Amino acid sequence: RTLNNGNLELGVHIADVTHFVAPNSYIDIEARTRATTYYLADRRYDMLPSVLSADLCSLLGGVDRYAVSIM
RNA sequence: UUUUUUUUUUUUUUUUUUUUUUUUUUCUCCUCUUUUUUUUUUUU
Image 1 (cartoon, protein in one colour):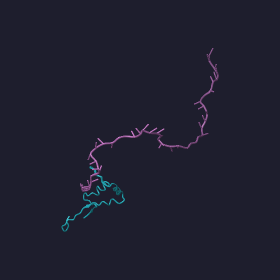
Image 2: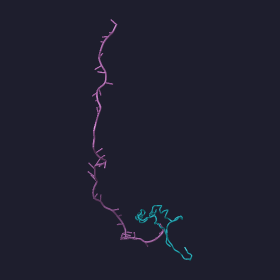
Image 3: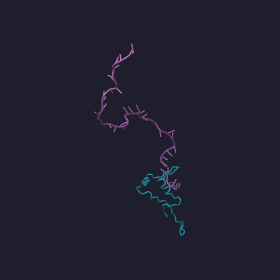
Image 4: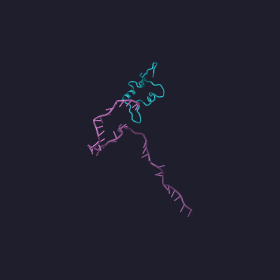
């Protein structure tokens, strides 16, 4: 955007998913095992269960969503 | 005018017992060919 002066503030905003993976959890060991999401060209393969992020983490609609905005 | 006699459905009951899925074979065996092995990168 522009501020009350005229210059161009820059910022990139990445989703802050750290609140649903606690250390030494079961989701955390799971992620530690499945290091990388694998993709074959029909479907994806969710690292998480299939509604924890595929409604609650995706920026859709205009509902509230925890994030991290560097600025 | 035709009297009298020739037995019948085996007797018995008031005996103890401390095991256990199955069960027993078949041999050694020539994997064909552009490669070192590619790899950052970004959009899920």
